[PDB]
Length: 10
Length: 99
Length: 99
Image: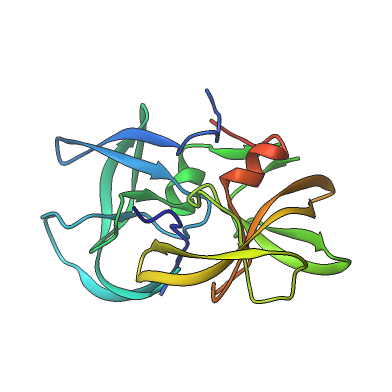
């Protein structure tokens, strides 16, 4: 399962 | 309350009358939910994560309850592996990172 | 400290005598840094999230100072867009989520 939920705005 | 990080910080949220599990995510600028139908106007956006970029739909002024806390804000919808509560709504509910 | 989430929670880290900046990420199980040379044996691993998976190198028992707090643990190295402190080391430095 994936484990790194970094997320950057548009 | 105070949430340990020995395990993923997963909480129940409520959006459009549906119950969902989401991750309290200080590494996310924004709140991003798995594909679902929401009402009203939207705009397409590209967001980046660990492995590249995904397309989402941006909906504004959506009510969402996050572990007992009423919030209203922007929700991005798309192919995220897990529902994510990002900083935009963590701030709204008064959530801090303490050590 | 009790860190607020108005801005991305980027903090000082010190690893192998190098001063870097990293994101405190409650949405990451593990810590991953941008490419760098670390000492000792490593194993290849894949880590995933939004946008898919990347190939990283896993080093063990690496000392790293995060916002002044000493940790020692497993550090992944690879093509992450930003240095990321994950739950593995957020726990070590005593982090909780509070609201």
